[PDB]
Image (tube, rainbow, N blue to C red; front, side, top):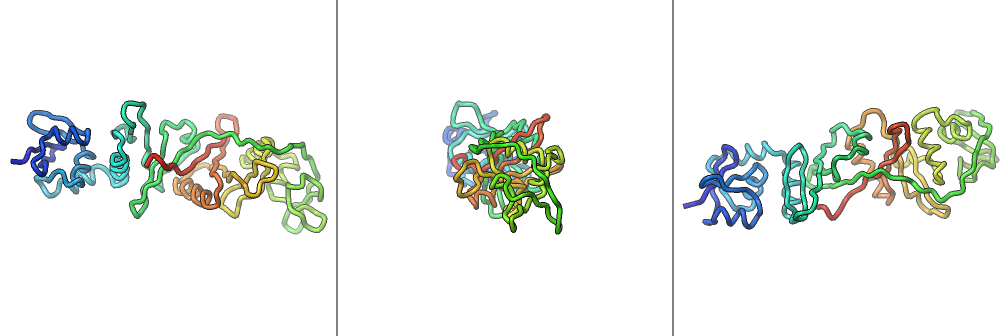
Amino acid sequence: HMEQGICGSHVFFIEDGKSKNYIIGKYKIGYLSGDNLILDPYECLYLYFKGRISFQNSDSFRDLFDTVTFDRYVAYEILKNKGYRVKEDSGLIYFRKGTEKPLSLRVMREYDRIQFSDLVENPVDYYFTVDEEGDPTVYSSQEIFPGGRNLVSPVSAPVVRMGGRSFGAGDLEWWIGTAFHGFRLLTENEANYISGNHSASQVDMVYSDLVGRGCIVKTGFKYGANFRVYLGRDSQHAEYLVSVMPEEERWYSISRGVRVASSVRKTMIYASIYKNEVRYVALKRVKDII
């Protein structure tokens, strides 16, 4: 007959006459309790797709599939097929190569509320995401410290608002502003900077912190970000794309940014005044893991 196990109220039969220890031995999952194999929701589902076990009741599959979510499941499977030892709990998916410290994966959903604070007090090493076509995406977020290699100087100039735009003299740091008939077309931020209003707003505070680091800040609107930043002198394209994370945030925004960024081969940086300081956090797609 078929040796069988159980996944919480769900009895299944091991296919092709395989010992319970075969499974345990081969997939490093589950355990024995009496003459039954005890599989957790994931493992059970996992093996079910492996064609390794059948179900007593028809509902079971669906039930367990609902129990664990598609998102969380796909993650489980991938990490599993890749080779890791997986284990979910506390609302996180832990995986290790074998005996080293595990790694926390955090399955996300476009409409989940994301916060900068979370990105800095990061309890998880990765953020996972599966799209509408079952395609997975892993991300990573770490506090960064932009290093501009540009000669910085204090710029306190006179600003004039005319025609609905702000302007300054045509000599300020060659890079600050734009050339317009001997004048210099300013951005609302650039105006506040040489105007001496660094505390105007949070985006202003970051703007200054940024320039002060040796970076050159130009508007990053053509990307949906507050600004683009060049780290070096002769920089053909801006390495960083920085955006100030507003009051409430939705993940797709984060997700979105990372895309329009990698596309233009730049890096998404999220700034915010965390604990009285202007810190930055880089978010990027992660390969290897999955």
